[PDB]
Amino acid sequence: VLQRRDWENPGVTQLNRLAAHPPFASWRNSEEARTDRPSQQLRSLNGEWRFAWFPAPEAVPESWLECDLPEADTVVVPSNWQMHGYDAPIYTNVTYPITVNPPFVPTENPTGCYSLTFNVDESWLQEGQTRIIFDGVNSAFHLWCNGRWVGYGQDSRLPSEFDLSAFLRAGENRLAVMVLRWSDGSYLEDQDMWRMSGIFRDVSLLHKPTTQISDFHVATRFNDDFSRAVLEAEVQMCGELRDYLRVTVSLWQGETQVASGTAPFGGEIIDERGGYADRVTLRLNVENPKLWSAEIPNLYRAVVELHTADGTLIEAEACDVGFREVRIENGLLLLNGKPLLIRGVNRHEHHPLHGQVMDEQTMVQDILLMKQNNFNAVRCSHYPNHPLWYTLCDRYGLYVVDEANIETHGMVPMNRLTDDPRWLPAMSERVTRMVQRDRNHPSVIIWSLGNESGHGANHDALYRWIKSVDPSRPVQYEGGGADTTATDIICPMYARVDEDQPFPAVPKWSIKKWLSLPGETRPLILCEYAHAMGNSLGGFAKYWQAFRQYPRLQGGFVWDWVDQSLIKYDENGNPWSAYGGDFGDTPNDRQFCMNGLVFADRTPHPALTEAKHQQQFFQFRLSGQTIEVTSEYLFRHSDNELLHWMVALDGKPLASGEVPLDVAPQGKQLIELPELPQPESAGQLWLTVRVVQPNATAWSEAGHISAWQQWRLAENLSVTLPAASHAIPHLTTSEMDFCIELGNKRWQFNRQSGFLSQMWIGDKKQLLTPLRDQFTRAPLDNDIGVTEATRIDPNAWVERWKAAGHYQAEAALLQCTADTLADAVLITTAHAWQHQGKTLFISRKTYRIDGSGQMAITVDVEVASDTPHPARIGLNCQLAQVAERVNWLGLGPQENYPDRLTAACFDRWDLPLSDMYTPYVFPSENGLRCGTRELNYGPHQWRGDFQFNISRYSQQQLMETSHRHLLHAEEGTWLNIDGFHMGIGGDDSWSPSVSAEFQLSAGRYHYQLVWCQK
Amino acid sequence: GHYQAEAALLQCTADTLADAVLITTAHAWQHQGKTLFISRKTYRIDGSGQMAITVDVEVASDTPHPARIGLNCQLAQVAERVNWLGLGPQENYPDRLTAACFDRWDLPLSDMYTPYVFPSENGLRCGTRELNYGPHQWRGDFQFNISRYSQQQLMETSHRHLLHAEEGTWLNIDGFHMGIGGDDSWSPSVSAEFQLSAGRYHYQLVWCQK
Ligand SMILES: CC(C)S[C@@H]1O[C@H](CO)[C@H](O)[C@H](O)[C@H]1O
Ligand SMILES: [Mg+2]
Ligand SMILES: [Mg+2]
Ligand code: NA
Ligand code: NA
Ligand code: NA
Ligand code: NA
């Protein structure tokens, strides 16, 4: 066993492991099978096991086989032993966490010894078969029962089952499991995620009778209009064949039995030697089947009864059946004859406290949030999931891409193993045993051959295997250029909408271009797009405009759902979010483990609302007073929807109403708005519509908003000249300052710096740091990319800004004058920002302080055309006051940026100061709000047309601090007011991704602000 | 009412600074009670004889995007040559300027007019940083056309041969000019990125004599 290193042999992936099959429970009562109640024949060993850690399997004491080690501790199972602290979890993206020397792994190979002492009743051993099921063991294990070696298993993400019948005794038994962290299986498990280990999914014991249902497959086929279906059920048995044996497959809609078939064993002739005597195929007619989709997840219950002709039950198995057809026709992916639009997300199995152990609550939380945010699909990135996931997807309604546990990203080249026939056996089992397990789940609509393993001949073989075995689902795979002979769907990752990326051998064409390449006919659905790392999803709207305009652009899966951050604790025992390198793990890929739409605790990032808005199922158009509503449902009518509409003048409500929605799938409804009264006062009328769900569903609460849109209506421009003031501001001059006085107010301009350095209301300072131009931002993850101090990526935005001296450019004064006017004082300034003799930016300003106390600031900036376009053009200052609330007229309520503001609505928003900061785990520029006409904070009011963020954290602190938990609130409030701000990008996070129309390239910029007190 | 809108003065003030005079104006263009455009300008005249013009325009969001945002006047001078640092030498528009090259161009006045058989706005040059004509020089970042025909005559005249040189020279200087389109000529064809929809517009000029 130590002799024979099976964990270093890709030719050995298991020993004595039983055949894979769909979920079993071996009910002995038909009614219990029908209702899906617990089964007495299926026991959970999810309790406290004994555990001990060793640096290598050579260090495991032989005594551990027969007896418990006193050194061992008592730990919860399922678990990852890294989450218990026995050794460290490693975060690496591409580079393998071990030396690349297949089939070999390190001699120092962390070994987890699990054991359990448990009871078996005599009744389980008198007759029949007792098997143990390990749903998940990472990454390879040897199993012993009562001292005796049972078997061995690889593949971390599929159940391993072993017959214990001959090993057990009635009463006290002991299981011993030696789990190896590293194996030859690790070479095929190089997914971009925390590398962990252990018995991390359910362990169970299953009792089956000797004469048993050993396998069953459910197929549903349809006539052209889906008014007729045949359910075909192939059922296999093990045990001794007998003439009196029968199978009954019955189909149920709730408590109504809809169809039933009974036959003895003995299939039709197959070839010259006969048929399968151990198999039967039952076929049931179903008239006007209720069809399954993510829109309406209609399910039936199939009960599979093995019994005698006279009617004694032997055992029953069961599954949920969803009637649906998935096919590709004329280059379109069809579900029930209708072209899908995939509103998808990739989802890793990750919990911040429990690692890679999944639980029902977290699973359900995820589904609810997904459906609540207009997602209809999920990709199992990048392995078969916990078996309950598929059940939940079946029941709530989500389309699933089921993906084999094969990723060889770190090989050179990427297909070095997948093109090697010696690795085909190992690969084949990871595909075959997934299909055998999951093939009865209606939620699974597409099979995937794995991820980032290049394109090798093994892919082509395994592609064809699934096509033979299961014609009911398309097979996709992205490796080796996303349009190879091993995929039914063009499935690129991070291909852009309009921009080609012509990498040699594996180009990523513009998705619109890819579709029409000579000879290309297939549908395109991105397996990964819109990399949601930190402040991201810039340009998301561009994808959806394209998905909606192009039939064959059928959507994609966002990368990804949830940040893979883990909880650590400080000296005060306070929790914080950790990423790569925070466990002494090295090499690592730092914050790249965090790419989620939600935080690890399932709190949303601002990007989620942008995804919800773009993935809406109702589209809107306005013509005069008529709203046109178009449904993008393919199957359901809008029978739990009403349209609320509201017209407001600069945030002030003027009229509202509601109209029920009554839209056929793909249909249109016209809504004529009543005559709206004219406003007296100036300003812009805005129309906002919202789709509300009056009733609760299985996935949402009463009053849930599923869609919205906004339009500008009439605008009445202000022509009224403000009331003339009788006071006139007084200018006081010193060598160091221009001071302006008006009533209880004072303004101070430093003549050496050229900036407003202080402001007084009554006697009190308003500024802690003078008002100064700013052209930089604390860099986003998209700005940073894959650059490092030891290995600069000169193409990354941050590195371009640094090398050009944007971050260390010092303001030099060119002009500072003061003129007294009739009813105002005018300060005129000019500055140059230079780096090593090169003039980067020029800023020319006037400040006009009139008798009404208002300060008008006009700013005109020049940006050298050959310097990298700047992150922002605006001002910043540190205010002295900390106020409770922030009130603004502009886009909100949530964080929004120029290329991620479609979700935001224009209105009057009022939030606590803390909501104006986004707690990204890796800190950066954040909390900006665009299209803002008025900002209110304490006694201050700023007016104009600007973008702003406001918080207790300076841009400097944000860029200097690598974790949110190390941030400290600074004195006062940092205000950044921008005339212009660069896009955030996110098409990917390892190359510049900000689109040209969102780069600040205009050369000359102008903005104006009015600063006053209310 | 774009063609018949009349200016209504909102503000006209003068200020003496240390080495300059500043004129501040604001106008509203209106049609039937509706305000289409607001123009706020400053004119800063210094000791060097330069007049700096700042222009800030508001366009009502429910009025159709205007063809241009600029200034015009009829100059008394008739000069032989037009000299400019900008895109040329030929007529060019925002959606048709890729062929034009940035350089120093010098043409006879009649080359700054394009004799389309059916007369319309014509002879614009974009991306112009400096324009010279007779005793005048304009600097900034603007589009212009210059000819002996007013926009009014061009629009009222159906055939090129019926046009007559007006007294002096008509100068149109635009901070912004709408695309010309052409995908077809029977439905609107100016693409959205070339429509003047920004709502608020800024441009600046310096008028002087060399
Ligand atoms: C060139 C590398 C950045 S590969 C890139 O890394 C990402 C990091 O989140 C994801 O894992 C993507 O799937 C992968 O293609
Ligand atoms: Mg092996
Ligand atoms: Mg990878
Ligand atoms: Na489409
Ligand atoms: Na990642
Ligand atoms: Na930082
Ligand atoms: Na004409």
Image (cartoon, grey):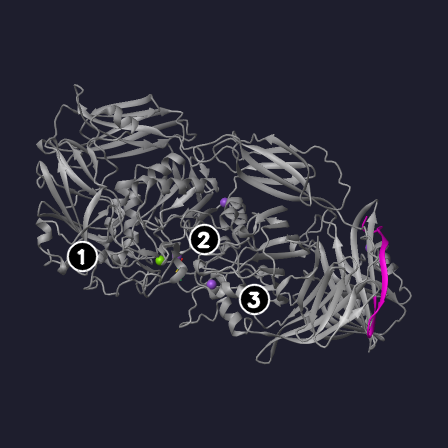
Specify the farthest residue to the bottom.
Answer: A837
C-alpha distance separating marks 1 and 2: 36 Å
Residue designated by label 1: A7
Res B180 visible: no
Disc 2: CA contacts within 10 A as few (<14), some (14-19) or many (>=20): many
Q: Quadrant of the N terminus of chain A?
A: bottom left
The disc, 3 or 2, on the residue closer to the chain's N-terminal end is 2
Kindly identify the amino acid type of the residue bearing the numbered disc 2: Tyr
Specify the farthest residue to the front.
Answer: A763
Disc 1: CA contacts within 10 A as few (<14), some (14-19) or many (>=20): many
Mark 3 and mark 1 in contact? Answer it, CB < 8 Å.
Answer: no
Q: Which residues are magenta?
A: B1-22
Disc 3: CA contacts within 10 A as few (<14), some (14-19) or many (>=20): many
- Residue A388 within the magenta-colored segment of the rendering: no
- Is residue A811 rendered to the left or right of residue A263? right
Q: Which mark is residue A529?
A: 2
| Percent of width and height locating residue A268 | 21, 31
Query: Do tags 1 and 2 sit on the same chain?
Result: yes
Q: Nearer the viewer, mark 1 or mark 2?
A: 1
Q: Ligand 1 closer than 8 Å to the CB at disc 2? A: no
Residue designated by label 3: A776
- Residue B9 within the magenta-colored segment of the rendering: yes
Q: Nearer the viewer, mark 3 or mark 2?
A: 3
| Percent of width and height locating residue A49 | 19, 46
